[PDB]
Amino acid sequence: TDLKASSLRALKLMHLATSANDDDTDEKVIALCHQAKTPVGTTDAIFIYPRFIPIARKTLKEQGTPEIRICTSTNFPHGNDDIDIALAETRAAIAYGADSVAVVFPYRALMAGNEQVGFDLVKACKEACAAANVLLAVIIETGELKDEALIRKASEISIKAGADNIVTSTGKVAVGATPESARIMMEVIRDMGVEKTVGFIPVGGVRTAEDAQKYLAIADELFGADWADARHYAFGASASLLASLLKALGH
Image (cartoon, rainbow, N blue to C red; front, side, top):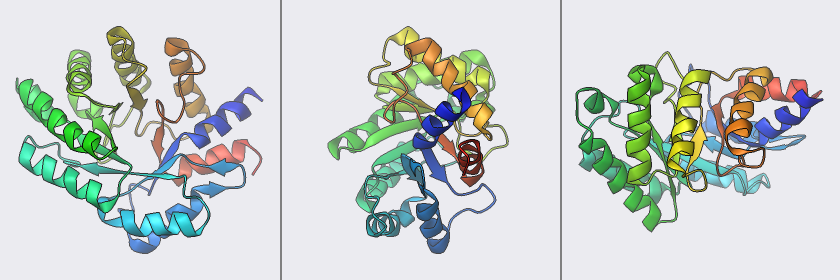
């Protein structure tokens, strides 16, 4: 029954996205909105491309779940180092009506030795989001950085630039989150003492109810059992994890 409790808890923290082998479509997003409403409760949000926000917002409203948030991505998935492009895309996502924007950190530029551009890019995008009461998350793409020191450095730059959440992965490269990269990023949150204002989102690597229980255990250990609420923790995953959480709950 410990598994059942963390399964329901993981479920309500989900940022439901379409399968990686599906991209997105007006009908597939309407379907996604329906799956986000289950017999035991709703996921916290959906994760979709910006152009589908307006139709997702109407679907969620008309099905009686206006409280499900809509998160989207910019500078995505490439993480290029052109700030003007990243800012313009972020402003468009806001105008579409997003509740949360996840900008991809310029991780290639960091790997090449540029720590400043990542700071300036996140800062410019956070400025636009804050001005519109939108949360800014930052994807650092742990699967491409690989090295522990680079994952810490990307996390530290993002936090100092004003990230409201830090995210492992885009979901568009082979390797997403792992327990180790997840631990590293949450330890930066702790070491910097910013756990009240910065949350964490593993993308990928969580496919079963047992995986989700393991990832939540890391959060409970580092910050206490109460820390991982919808504002500070989320699982960026697809319908396959959701079905495993529902199954563990007997549905």
